[PDB]
Amino acid sequence: ALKDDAVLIAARGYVYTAAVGTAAPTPSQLKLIDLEHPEAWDRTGWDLVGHTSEDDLPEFGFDGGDSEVRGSWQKKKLREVETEEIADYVVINLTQFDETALELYFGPNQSATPGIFGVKSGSVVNERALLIVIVDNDVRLGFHARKASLKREDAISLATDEFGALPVRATFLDYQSYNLYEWIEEDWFNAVDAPVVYLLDLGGATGGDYTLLVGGKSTGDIAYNANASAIKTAIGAVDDGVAESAWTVTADGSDFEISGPLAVALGVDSTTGGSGVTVDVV
Amino acid sequence: ALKDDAVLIAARGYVYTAAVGTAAPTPSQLKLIDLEHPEAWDRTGWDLVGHTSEDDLPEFGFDGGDSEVRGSWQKKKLREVETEEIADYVVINLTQFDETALELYFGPNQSATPGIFGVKSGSVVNERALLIVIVDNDVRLGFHARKASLKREDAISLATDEFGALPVRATFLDYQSYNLYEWIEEDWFNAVDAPVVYLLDLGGATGGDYTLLVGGKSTGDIAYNANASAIKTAIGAVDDGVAESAWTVTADGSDFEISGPLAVALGVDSTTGGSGVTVDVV
Amino acid sequence: ALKDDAVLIAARGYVYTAAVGTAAPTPSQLKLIDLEHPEAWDRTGWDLVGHTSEDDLPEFGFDGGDSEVRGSWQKKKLREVETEEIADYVVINLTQFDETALELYFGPNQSATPGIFGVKSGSVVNERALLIVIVDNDVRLGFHARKASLKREDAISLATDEFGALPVRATFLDYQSYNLYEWIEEDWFNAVDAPVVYLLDLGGATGGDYTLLVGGKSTGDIAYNANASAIKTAIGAVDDGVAESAWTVTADGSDFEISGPLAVALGVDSTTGGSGVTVDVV
Amino acid sequence: TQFDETALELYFGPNQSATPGIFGVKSGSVVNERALLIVIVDNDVRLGFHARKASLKREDAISLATDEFGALPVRATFLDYQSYNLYEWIEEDW
Amino acid sequence: ALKDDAVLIAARGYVYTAAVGTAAPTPSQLKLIDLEHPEAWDRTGWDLVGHTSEDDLPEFGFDGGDEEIADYVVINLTQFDETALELYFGPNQSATPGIFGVKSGSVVNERALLIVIVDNDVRLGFHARKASLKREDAISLATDEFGALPVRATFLDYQSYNLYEWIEEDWFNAVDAPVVYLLDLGGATGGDYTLLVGGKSTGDIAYNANASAIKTAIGAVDDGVAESAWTVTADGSDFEISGPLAVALGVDSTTGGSGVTVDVV
Amino acid sequence: AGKLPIVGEVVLPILRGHEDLSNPISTVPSLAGVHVGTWVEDIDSRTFPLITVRRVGGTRSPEHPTLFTQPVVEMTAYSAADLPTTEQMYEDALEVLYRAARLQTKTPAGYLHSVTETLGASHGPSPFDRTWRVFGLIRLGIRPPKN
Amino acid sequence: AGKLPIVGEVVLPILRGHEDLSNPISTVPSLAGVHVGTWVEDIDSRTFPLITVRRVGGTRSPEHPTLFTQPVVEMTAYSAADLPTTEQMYEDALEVLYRAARLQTKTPAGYLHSVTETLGASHGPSPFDRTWRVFGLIRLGIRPPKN
Amino acid sequence: AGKLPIVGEVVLPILRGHEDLSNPISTVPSLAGVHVGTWVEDIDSRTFPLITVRRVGGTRSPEHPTLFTQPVVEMTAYSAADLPTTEQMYEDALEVLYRAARLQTKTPAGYLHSVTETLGASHGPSPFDRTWRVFGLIRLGIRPPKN
């Protein structure tokens, strides 16, 4: 369905890590928690990875997903099959060089002397839970993976007039019975269907008349009048191709919540003899 | 032949989905329905896929189609053979992050929890009927595929000053004896010679109270003392999406010519004078 | 030889199709036919494919043609051999979506219902004779293929601010004993063209004399009263010059025509009563 | 950039029908070998280049454009002829 | 000879089996039947086998050479329905719903076989009255391609019939009638035209020339025997020409009409 | 297909809310009573608020010159009220052009096909005594009126 | 082939609808009675409406400088009537160029081979009295006469 | 959900530090008592220091024109004190915009979604007697209010 408030532009992205299996903040907490201070919030165990750059975001990707259409000598185009298993990942450009931000990139340091971080040769196991919170005005679309394997995506960038960077790639993996990763936002996922209603604001008994668009076509002139069938049968029968039985208008008190398959709006209000029929708003 | 009104510059493209095999609007309905509220249509089951970037269209594509000329050392060119049969698809960049937008990209939600959308590992079967309507001018070139497999074309895109997007590729697959896909436009494909007329007979004038069904929808009833303007107002008052102004009705004494945007037929018959005022033929 | 009238800038290209093997209009008819109306030609059977752009032309191409130079352990650079045969084709962008322009792209309409054009899942054979007339001022270079096989060159293009397009590739194939394809214009091919011949012109023969350039150099001054052998011998004062053998002059016009192996033009003159003039036309 | 018969014969090989006003092409491939001379001009220098046997083939398809001249791109490949050189540069002073 | 019409690509095809000895559709039925639904054929008795593999098509092999050859077909099935397991393993050894059971050792398994190879409206058929069915090799399984049950059908003699028929109405035991070329002069209002025969032009033919004059204008250089290799016969306004060499239009120079020939191959 | 119109015969019915070309006062409810035209009247006749739309460039399309065109229109809002009211009146004019484009709005002279901004709303000096100007350039696509 | 012409000897017969160069009134139905020229006449004989064509400048083609050339002309239209009539007159003049190019029209001086706007019809200040002005740039293409 | 505002209804509450649009002096600690507004008051009412915000360009977003827009504002700081105080005051204002964008600051007319300079703190000549001026262009980005 064509809901506007679910459209997203990512303004900034916070990235947090924790020991493998750690639970994210719940969908209702994610609307209230202070993103700058993960040591303070109810769901203990998370920490910020470090200064990611201000003008870019954690970059999603996948390897695999190479997909092909297959059949038989009898019938062609029978089904589509994935020829390589899709492998989701995220890239994070940390710009911070203290021990906690090197540890994500190199794995744990293999030297214990004050002031030195040293690396052993070959492979390393370096795995954490990952929480990303993508922020846009009041929208806070969270993303959580209970195990991610964190690896060198490219060599350390250094530049004379652009910030140095430690690009890590987090690849998502199955951890016991849990999902591979989860998107978190309370208003969007598994929520109640919340059907649209249009508020006919008539300010009580008034002199004169007004018009309503239904589906972008005008019904006839409507005076200040009785409700129920006397408005429902003026909302219906606009040569709209929809029967009156698809619409509802109800005992709503002062102002009326019209609902049905088409959108509705006012055309003109000339109900000048008092408070008027001034709005139609959702 | 050249046709200045068959030349097309796609201004906006609506995209709808439904359960596999679901029928699209007929060519004569596609000129009359509104495109914004699928719950108003006669063909129930369609719903809008979501917001799409409004400077862009559904991007058609194919792979395969690799073809080459073959012969024998006697005769050097005699067939062009298609070495890899065309696998045909459309790419749709949704910009919503609503649940009903993510289900096209990830397949069904794997969690029961309010406010969470969960993703499992491995391939998913995810396939839908697909209807696209391409709008230009007063033209509405529709496109319908009864079965399309939906897969992730690329990872989720996020940017700091361009909308977030999650691209799906719909690949067409054949289904029962039906076509792979169909283009829908009444003016252009299998077109009749321009006028069509229905002859409503009047010789049975001892009469009764017959009725017409217009596009399958009833006019109420009409008494045998009929007149051209009176039956134009009757037909023109059927609640079907199109006004009295679209219909042309004229007389030759013994019958009326009826013509307009939709099919006309007699419903319930009631007449004393045999068939003579209950005949309606082309 | 250099031929300034045989240098082409194709301004526009008209593409026509017909049933396989049908003949193009003859080389003398391409000067007289009306390209907008193939329904009116003496050589009936052709139809114009539809609106192609005003900005571009049918694009010639080929696959194959890869050639190698071969020899022996004795003599190293003996023969050039063609390792894959030239497969020769034209690409046409149609920009109208009428049935008669979808049929060239998808093959025949697979559905009989009014307002629907449907496609089946398999390969299709779709063959035409193809005529292209390529226009530049009064030059109308034709191109004709007795059989061409028409295939989808790319997916349907749709765009917000440039015209929608149906790109077809026509590949040429041998039909019976005919040529693969033919170029057509009466003035250029198999024509018996005349030598370049230079015409002298003069005032009323009142004054003294005039000079002629022959190739890059001048002969001497000569009078209005001179005999053909005298002016032919004055032209014969040149590098390859043999008077009464290499050059020819025949006095067919009242003022002489010169024919021979170098260009001829006026220099300085003093033949009062008009002017000395020279041009390469008869 | 020229389209009369004598400019097409370099590109397609000799024409395959006798009809006045038509140039016809047959399928397959053609032996179209010629001697080639080029005279590069600069200053009042005339650096000549000569090959006694070159094989001429289509280098690419015919170019056509709405504001650039049409063209027939031939490639001449040099092949040795009996006892002669593969090609020769000709200039008296150099 | 050189039937360009009869060069085959196996673009799609179908495989059917039946009880031993069952007859295939006749050559004139095969041009017209619906291949998806063999239950609806007038030549009833045939059951359509499952989806055969898209890339490993039937191999019409043989084993012998010089001892005497046995012909076979290897067919890759790609379906795990009972209709396909019965060909690979032989008849089901268990009566319980939902189970297909296999006994040890060899089992007799014999069926009639029909194969139809379609291309584009040609439909070459192949039919064998009696085939013995065996496992060719292991069941193929993969994570990214359809699993396959390859079977060997070996042909065996039955009741004095052939081992197998190839069935196609156009190609086998045809009438072999010669080609004829139609000299359709169109309006023919005046002037001249020339044919060319085997690539050589005839040189001069008037718009009103009779069949004998055309037969004498043919007989160019390099002709067959000038006036007895070539048959020319009129019908309507036109002539049918036939003989040992190909005939085509060379140069029309007639004063009105939409053409000068229409020609068979 | 009929001839392509001058850009004023399409843009003005969209901003005015009626296809009577003889009456320049708008009735579109977001900017009702605004005088919408192409040429600013004599000081004894002119009324503020005022919107001026003026052709400033944009060719026919090269693909098919007689089938689609992309005029560039300088749109200018003027008022005697205050600068914020002149800004909101220009915004309320974009919000009408973008909606009228989203629908492919028909007019007697042609169809408005698409709308885009090549220079967004910007404040500038006004040539009229005690008024504010806000202006920008819209590139907008037009199609022939069928027929 | 003859010499390449100056652009006025080709464009003016295409806009005027006759090959008589001595008679500046056009007769093509879309422009019946407008005066088409390259130079605005003295005020004692100047007659509106008028279309002024002049070369803003574009090169010979480098491929063959003697065989094809691409002159840019500034085309302008003036009227004493109103701005809509001046826009409509420029549109109706440009529609003649886009047709006369498609038909490859012969003129005694050369052929109009192709047409392209490089700056579309646009409103600007007029040099004289009551009149309005609309102008743009067209890159033409010209081929020499077949002599 | 909501409608996009004129740019002043978003950035003025963010530079002022209060949602009361009637009270132009800022209360933000780095700008205490600076007058902030679109338009410079008459000479009998001017006070310095002063910041002014003018829209100079920047379109609606082309892919959803009703949901996001990127107005370019010229921001200009004036002082009667000295040039260092003027460029300090401009930096101390630009620090408020970069913080208010990072915090996604909700304003009753919309959300300040992002901030980006396109010219930075250029010194220039002032039109007012004994005052320094520094100015720059900021491409903002703003989202409509939820309802």
Image (spheres, coloured by chain):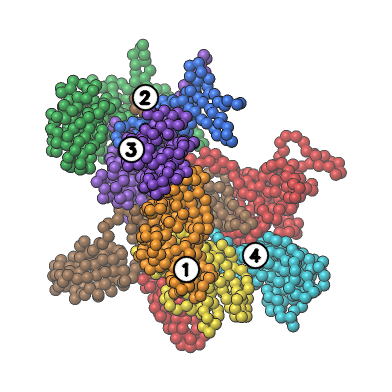
Chain colours: A red, B brown, C purple, D blue, E green, F yellow, G orange, H cyan
Front residue (pair D33, G4): G4
The amino acid beneath tag 1 is Glu
Q: Is residue D79 left or right of residue H71?
A: left
- Callout 2: chain: B
Are the residues under marks 2 and 3 on the same chain? no
Q: Quick one: label 4, few (<14), some, or many (20+) residues within 10 Å?
A: many
Chain of the residue on which disc 3 is drawn: C
In contact (CB < 8 Å): disc 3 and disc 1 = no
Q: Disc 2 designates what residue? A: B73
Q: Which numbered circle lies on residue G41?
A: 1
Instruction: Mark 4 vs mark 1: give the one in front.
Output: 1
Task: Give the answer, above or below, for where A107 lies relative to B94.
Answer: above
CB within 8 Å, label 2 to label 3: no
Q: Is residue H114 left or right of residue C63?
A: right
Q: Report, in whole angstroms, how far the alpha carbon at label 2 lies from the one at label 3.
A: 60 Å
> Residue at the location (46% across, 54% down)?
G6
Q: Find numbered disc 3 in the image and state the secondary structure of the residue it sits on.
A: loop
Q: Is residue F94 above or below residue A170?
A: below
Using the numbered discs, state the Cα–Cα distance from disc 3 to disc 1 in whole angstroms. Answer: 52 Å
Q: Residue A100 appears at what percent x and percent y? A: 77, 48
The residue indicated by pointer 4 is H72
Whether discs 1 and 2 lie on one chain: the answer is no
Chain for numbered disc 1 = G
Marks 4 and 1, how far apart at CA: 47 Å
